[PDB]
Image (cartoon, coloured by chain):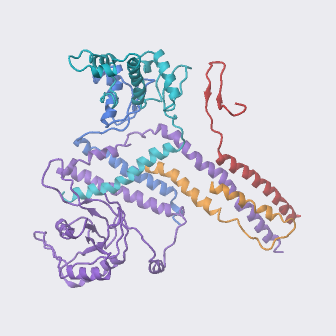
Chain colours: A orange, B blue, C purple, D red, E cyan
Amino acid sequence: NYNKAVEEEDKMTPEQLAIKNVGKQDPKRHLEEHVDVLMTSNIVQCLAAMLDTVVFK
Amino acid sequence: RPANHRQLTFEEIAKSAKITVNEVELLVMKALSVGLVKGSIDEVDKRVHMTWVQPRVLDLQQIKGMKDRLEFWCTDVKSMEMLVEHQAHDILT
Amino acid sequence: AVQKVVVHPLVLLSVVDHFNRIGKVGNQKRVVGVLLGSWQKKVLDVSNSFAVPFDEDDKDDSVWFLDHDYLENMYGMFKKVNARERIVGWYHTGPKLHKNDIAINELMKRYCPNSVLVIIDVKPKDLGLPTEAYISVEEVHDDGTPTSKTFEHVTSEIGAEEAEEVGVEHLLRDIKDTTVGTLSQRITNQVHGLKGLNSKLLDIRSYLEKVATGKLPINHQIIYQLQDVFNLLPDVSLQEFVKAFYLKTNDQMVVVYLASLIRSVVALHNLINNKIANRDAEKKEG
Amino acid sequence: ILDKKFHGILDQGEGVLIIFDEPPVDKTYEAALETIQNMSKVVDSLYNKAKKLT
Amino acid sequence: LLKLFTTMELMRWSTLVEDYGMELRKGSLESPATDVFGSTEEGEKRWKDLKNRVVEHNIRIMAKYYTRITMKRMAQLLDLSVDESEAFLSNLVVNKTIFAKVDRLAGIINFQRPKDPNNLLNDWSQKLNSLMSLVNKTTHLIAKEEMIHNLQ
């Protein structure tokens, strides 16, 4: 629910990348901090889904 | 029996426990009062379900021949640990 | 009923330099010392200790030496530096016990509500946990002998209190915080799988030596009553988690739905703005 | 049912009314509808694409 | 009374007639019987409030083995009919003390819990209870191991 509630303001950025021609000084980049959290957090969740099939046999 | 079919029918109960169909329910509700076994006994099939129990006192032949569970556990969870790690081997990184 | 304490390895570096003393004083091979501290709750913290000049005969192993020139007036010193950090227990090395440990505990039990013999680890290569605690126990038996006093496993950990990393995390110079799920989890897989299953080899050591050459605690009262807990699920063919397999579909539900949806947003994340930066760099480099 | 005062299923064959409900899943709803908005935004970036190309 | 308060020990109600009715066959104090069951339009309501006890309190002792029962077996266990069963089902469902759901497509129904209302709770309860048991295991298997290997 964190990873949706902040993803809508994550996607409020490509509208700001539509500057039709160019009207924005430098990238002002907010791509990150929601790659990595999703990445390692759901690595943890998939290896947790491993963990029952690990401990059981 | 270590095996499954832990939704046991009442049949062995009413045969070898010298009890009747109307009294298997008391046989296990008095055991709920006892508190060593707390089965979720079926009553659409009348099956006496097995949950967790208080096992024994001593099975010295099975204290010796628990290897088929203990060493089973040891080498097989070890081997499958080696297999999970062996499929994710070269992301040692 | 004691779970865990908080451990500062600072006076374990005092264990280290008394481990430097014993290598060059004489015949005393093992490090035996006295563990100060203060019961705060079932959780606890330790700030200081000290190391007795101790000898122990190999013949009739109940030969202790805990000098009161080294206890009483050094206790006056340790009381003068602070009133808070008083006695809480003691410590010796190895993992097991020697015989005289019970009487060394009962010596300083007269000062303390519960003196603890935390058995300490100077050359750590172990498979389980570090230094671990033992509380005063009266469990005697179901037989009714004169009261048992062998201090039972009432465990401990190595807790971290507060700052100290001015020293410590400057003294690291090597280590890194793994952003968990970056082979930290398989460090844990290695350690807990291999080190719990050769702990299970210690258990087969118990369940083989106590079968071949092992008596009275052979089925003490906690071997079989825990073979229950071993008999949660030991079964034969594939152990048939018939409920739990569609329930594990219900498990894998959340995980791979977040994989599909969320990782498709991750595809959108990297790919779209990567194409922006990429192709802008590419042809606007002209 | 059509006014959501009553959440379940009636019957005529066996004559068995059965009340149950579970509507809200934001794990599906919020995520996938925000991806629809994401795809609209990527279509809005398609002209940055079609502008850098031609 | 007190043995009938703990699990209620599904006795014969005519042995309750024995116990609570041969109190009038007392060559001593009958003022207990006179005050309690000597009443008629209050004491008869106490007799049937004790039939309410057998249904009420014995549904609360039988609430364990449900999520599967027919209706005839519930008549054969509540020590009464199916019509007395349905009247008692009525007044105890308007009691709504523990969440009932009864239906006669074939009659396999019962007084019940909210009927396993959750998803992953099963993973939580089963696997985390059993596996945190299995992580406390090694922590006191080293306990047992050291304490038995002091000697042998």
- Extreme left residue here? C60
Q: Position of residue E136 (x, y in %)?
A: 36, 54
Horizontally, residue C73 falls left or right of residue C266, namely left
Relative to C72, is D35 above or below?
A: above
Horizontally, residue D5 falls left or right of residue D48, namely left
Of residues E90 and B73, the one drawn nearer to the viewer in this rendering = E90
Relative to B17, is B84 above or below?
A: below
Q: Position of residue B26 (x, y in %)?
A: 33, 26
Q: Quadrant of residue D21?
A: top right
Relative to E121, is C35 above or below?
A: below
Q: Residue at x 51, y 56 (%)?
A: B87
Q: Position of residue C283 (x, y in %)?
A: 82, 70
Q: Residue at x 66, y 54 (%)?
A: C262
Of residues C23 and E45, the one drawn nearer to the viewer in this rendering = E45
Horizontally, residue D25 falls left or right of residue C81, namely right
- Tell how many labels: 0
Q: Quadrant of residue C12?
A: bottom left
Relative to B46, is C7 above or below?
A: below
Query: Can you see residue B39?
Result: yes
Q: Residue at x 41, y 22 (%)?
A: E49
Of residues B9 and B81, the one drawn nearer to the viewer in this rendering = B9
- Extreme right residue here? D54
Q: Position of residue E129 (x, y in %)?
A: 42, 47
Query: Can you see residue C215?
Result: no
- Extreme bottom residue here? C24
